[PDB]
Length: 259
Ligand SMILES: NS(=O)(=O)c1ccc(OC[C@@H](O)C[Te]C[C@@H](O)COc2ccc(S(N)(=O)=O)cc2)cc1
Ligand SMILES: [Zn+2]
Image (tube, rainbow, N blue to C red):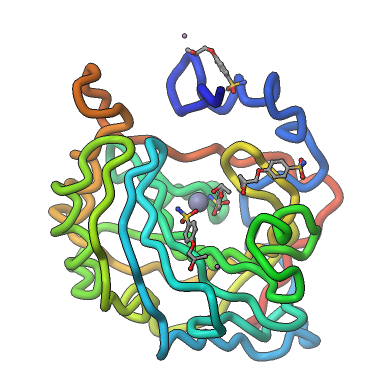
């Protein structure tokens, strides 16, 4: 059974023993060297179309919390940019730190942000998420950095439900949540081919990482850090530092949408 996590004994340094692709050619996250990334004029405009998004539920899966969406139709899709065709939103989640100086998976010139939001989408040409993760162009993950400063009003509904999903396996109704309230003003981005950042580490992701971070309050991120990795009735282990460090870039080019 799966026993990977983020501890000294089951963390990122151990994952390769059960998931050998951990040492593969297109692993994520990476450090984004802003001076080596090249502006690509061939990139088409990015289209985030979340007007008809239908959120369903929020789940503590023991690694993060996921806000799940209805992906049975083209209700909330990502198109354009580096992408061919239509990618449907299935879930979002975050990665965060024990302190504000760490938490993000991607880094920018080695800078770590307090957290990183992942909006996960699958390519509709493969029919379902499970088929899409088997394909090199199966997923598109929109990554958004979080810095600590002013509160993000569009995050507060998420923060306020977390005490109902404290432990692994707990879920709560989470209808009528608008993920557009989690975006920054600018859609300027970097893109590169990579992987899932947790086991099974499948090399199926087109990464689109926004340049502009969102600001969240210290009080908002403190509520993320009150979650637990453990199940109810197990010793309490705070859900903090659920991020994989930067992996080798190898033979990849990061492309910028902006000058
Ligand atoms: N035979 S094989 O092709 O090698 C193969 C091996 C394992 C397979 O397991 C498929 C299952 O879907 C488990 Te992949 C869904 C799981 O919910 C994780 O999803 C994530 C979503 C986003 C991110 S992130 N942080 O990068 O945004 C991270 C994880 C399927 C095929
Ligand atoms: Zn993630």
